[PDB]
Image (cartoon, coloured by chain):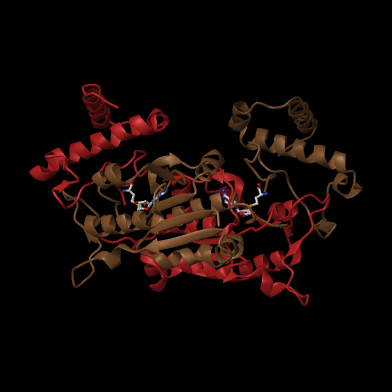
Chain colours: A red, B brown
């Protein structure tokens, strides 16, 4: 085992999406990744298990009820033992990116608090949360999907998780990935770049790095401006741009 | 019914995460949102239902097998009838944001192609995809979570989906949301801003807009620079900054 993740959520079963399918399901099944959930609903005392409450100053929407949510978080922290980083999923937190992913991957223990409705009391955040994280500048119905997004992302780093089907993928080296092809040789009248059929290992390597650089330049120029390229990368980028400026475009 | 979403995925059951829980589950259960899936595996012809293949030029990783994936996509398009926008979930696509969400919400029909492994043949993308979308600058194990992220986001716009527990949330007006409080009056020694207890509707309104502006200014200044504030917003932003510059900080 390498990573334990505690989760606070009103919809615990949603997490089977990552715990029972694909490489993440595999990682969980083989104890490389542990995911335990605590539902605030189970900590309610009223006959109707109320997990929401009215915000002071009213307004539209409801907030998660404090007591049930706080008790679930404390219970989760009790099981986590010491060293767990408590994270609140929020569109107002640090926007996630590969760098943030690798940073989060360093933790051995995590606790992810998933909100619902309008969110949670701001005092809870100040007193129970270590960091706030967002998966992007958009709003979802709850923290569950974002929490799973975070888990899936950091799971790719746990040793033994990925197989023969990672270090070449987008943002890995700060660059987008190159295009890839497979059978058939001709698809809808389109062929595979001859070099990928030539079997020239070194040439194929350069073609891929060149494409990785060109695509980053064309789609995410700001990324290039941020990276410090090696001599070879600066040479392949020059060639990729030169090749592009040599052809007609749409 | 208002939106039909066709999905191509090797793990169809993952989608129960959104189709059977919360407001999205509710929206599906009540036919406001329709989600149909097609698994490429069901289109395989070999004894072992192979859905992956070796990339030309080799390298690490596998690609989704073309024929099974292409047949699933065509079948999905056949059911979609005409007018469906075909989307490929990819970390190299247009980065998602609220604006993009509202744009995507205009479509009545969507088809979301979820990749696995290293991805899919670049020719398939050129011949079957209308647009590529990313949920953020990080890499996940598959397109399923990103696809669900997209669905959940656009579902918030379908009429009848959200209830009394949306227009006040972050990015709605381009600004982050304000803090919110609920019972108890005192939490861990922390009290609720008196104004939220005063019951002064107009004052509470300004407090919320001011906080929304201050938080955006402090956390996402670039967003402010992009927005065109109204007179009242420019006045409340001035006050929020002035109030902040009047206190000690950590
Ligand atoms: N972009 C995203 N990243 C992480 N969590 C998100 C998210 N979008 C929504 N959430 C989660 O889903 C919940 C319901 S959305 C309510 C959001 C809140 N009023 C705001 O504007 O800050 C939030 O409490 C949060 O836990
Ligand atoms: N940020 C994200 N947004 C949308 N889809 C993503 C994603 N991260 C991963 N994927 C999805 O999961 C799949 C496995 S990840 C393989 C990614 C590919 N080599 C690249 O670098 O472009 C991708 O095919 C895609 O469908």
Quadrant placement of the C terminus of chain A: top left
> Is residue B65 or residue A46 the one in the foreground?
B65
Question: Residue reaching furthest front?
Answer: B81
Quadrant placement of the N terminus of chain A: bottom left
Q: State whether residue B18 appears in this view.
A: yes
Q: Position of residue B250 (x, y in %)?
A: 71, 39
Q: Residue at position x 62%, y 68% from top?
A: A76
Q: Is residue A162 above or below residue B92?
A: below
Q: Is residue A104 left or right of residue B219?
A: left
* Residue B125, quarter of the rendered image: top left
The mark tally for this picture is 0
Q: Position of residue A55 (x, y in %)?
A: 79, 54
Q: Residue at position x 50%, y 46% from top?
A: A96
Q: Position of residue A22 (x, y in %)?
A: 37, 65
Q: Position of residue A154 (x, y in %)?
A: 44, 56
Question: Residue reaching furthest bottom?
Answer: A47
Q: Is residue B231 left or right of residue A207?
A: right
Q: Is residue A150 left or right of residue A74?
A: left
> Is residue B239 or residue B51 the one in the foreground?
B51
Q: Residue at position x 69%, y 53% from top?
A: A118
Q: Is residue B89 above or below residue B30?
A: above
> Is residue B83 or residue B221 the one in the foreground?
B83
Q: State whether residue A157 appears in this view.
A: no
């Amino acid at each position: 085992s390498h990573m334990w993740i505690g989760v606070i959520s009103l919809f615990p079963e949603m997490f089977k999406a990552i715990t029972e399918f694909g490489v993440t399901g595999r990682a969980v099944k083989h104890n490389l990744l542990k995911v335990e959930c605590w539902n605030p609903r189970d900590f309610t005392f009223d006959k109707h298990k109320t997990v929401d409450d009215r915000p002071y100053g009213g307004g539209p929407g409801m907030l998660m009820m404090v007591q049930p949510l706080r008790d679930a978080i404390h219970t989760a922290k009790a099981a986590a033992g010491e060293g767990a980083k408590v994270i609140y999923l929020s569109p107002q937190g640090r926007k996630l990116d590969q760098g943030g992913v690798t940073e989060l991957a360093q933790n051995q223990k995590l606790i992810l608090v998933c909100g619902r409705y309008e969110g949670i009391d701001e005092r809870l955040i100040q007193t129970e949360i270590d960091e706030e994280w967002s998966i992007g500048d958009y709003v979802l119905t709850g923290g569950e999907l974002p929490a799973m997004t975070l888990i899936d992302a950091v799971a790719r780093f746990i040793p033994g998780v990925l197989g023969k089907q990672a270090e070449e993928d987008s943002f890995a080296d700060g660059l987008l990935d190159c295009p890839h092809y497979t059978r058939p040789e001709v698809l809808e009248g389109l062929t595979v770049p001859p070099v990928l059929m030539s079997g020239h290992h070194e040439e194929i390597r350069k073609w891929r790095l060149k494409q990785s650089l060109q695509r980053t330049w064309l789609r995410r120029p700001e990324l290039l401006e941020g990276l410090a390229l090696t001599d070879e990368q600066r040479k392949l980028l020059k060639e990729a741009q030169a090749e592009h400026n040599s052809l007609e475009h749409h």
